[PDB]
Length: 540
Ligand SMILES: NC(=O)c1cn([C@@H]2O[C@H](CO)[C@@H](O)[C@H]2O)c2ncnc(N)c12
Ligand SMILES: [K+]
Image (cartoon, rainbow, N blue to C red; front, side, top):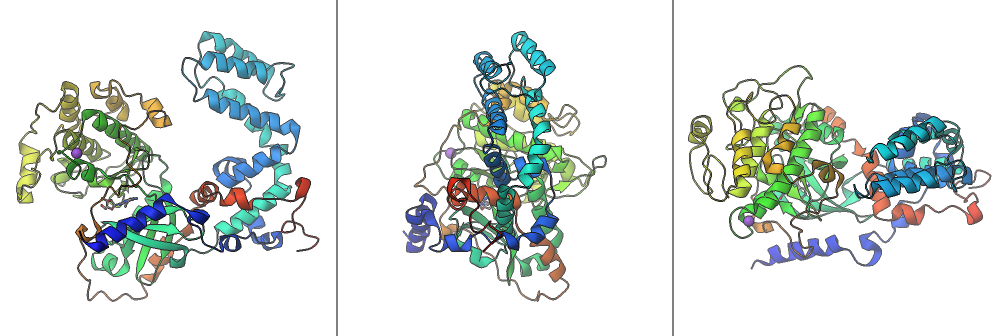
């Protein structure tokens, strides 16, 4: 046992768990100290006054507007209804009826205890007629839309005039603070990327755990990849999906550019396939993972963006067992009506169209989904052996010519979804046609997978990683780069560095404050709902 291997993980595991100060800096209350509201006049001018952004999408602003609504009983009742419609939207599909009636009898009646007077009588009656017809979780959608149409009016304008929006401006003043290497503390390397290495890092003030994808400036230049780096960053930010790694920071360094990403302490799937017992795992695990991978691919294809690099090592597991797609550097956004043409990908996972320099759309991803489902069931790549040292020229040859081979491990449904997703003609490939992912979601393979409860987070993952385990190779077994030489950086690269490095992302940052309880603890106003001194303009 090598000491460096041991110490590297015992440290990571200690920070991961916690536990005094929750892992925060000793002076975190001074770092995140609110400015005086008099310091937020610039923000006052530039902030866009949007109800949906300031009172729902922006996490801290959604809680500050609810705190304002709960200051007046006339507005709190609405917040109660909306919260009640949320429960009904995630309650048992059989108990919908009784709970839908509870809401109807609690909020939408002439003398209901918490009567909402802006929903509209026709609407409640329409909703009350459909109550019987059949109970669906979308039943109350319109009622809540009527509440939001009323809250975006006078209530929103009064919030903007309140001390709670002043507090939001303070929070935003903190959000926009600069990011730097001193903002985080780096831990062990979790894996090696294309331009650098992924590490585990921790925000020093909040204690939140992340993963830093370092992209070494010299390496980006040596390999002409300045557009791949920017594309990955812009992509990660544009996308929103519970099944794709999300971006929270993006800062620059003397020698590298960094992407702070969601940490996946469960590890990558290649590790769970080859370094944890027998090759491959059970179909049930493969079912769940393939389903979420598909969901993540549906979220990407909504923005007409292809991935082109689907392989086990780019699928990760989180604290609970759900997965996300990780290296979006090879992804591109095809023109909504045009197709692309580039031989990009990892051998054994490049689809036939991408192998003959043909032109393709969002197609090579469904080939990659089949390559995965096969590898998770069998224990090898469909067209290559585990440790076969086959020249990749031949690996190509096989995928276009030979046909994959199945075994007793594959079920009838598992063998079909693979054989349809591995169709060597894009037109005739499952999902590559017209319906889209919906043709996959019906396949006999997923005959027991409710992609609705899956996309909602109701299904429990099959495998749950153990907190006191590092589902990763040892640090000394991670491959290393070869020192770059002769690529001395200059000025013309400074324009791309400034465009890449945009600081913190708004919504992730605010979530980080909520989760770490920094918001909870520092978002204190005065006694009996009085102006605190940092919001009082009569004196600092
Ligand atoms: N999203 C990423 O870029 C990540 C890459 N790795 C590791 O780094 C390796 C790079 O291929 C993977 O196999 C993982 O072990 C990660 N490990 C944890 N969280 C992450 N967000 C990543
Ligand atoms: K295994």
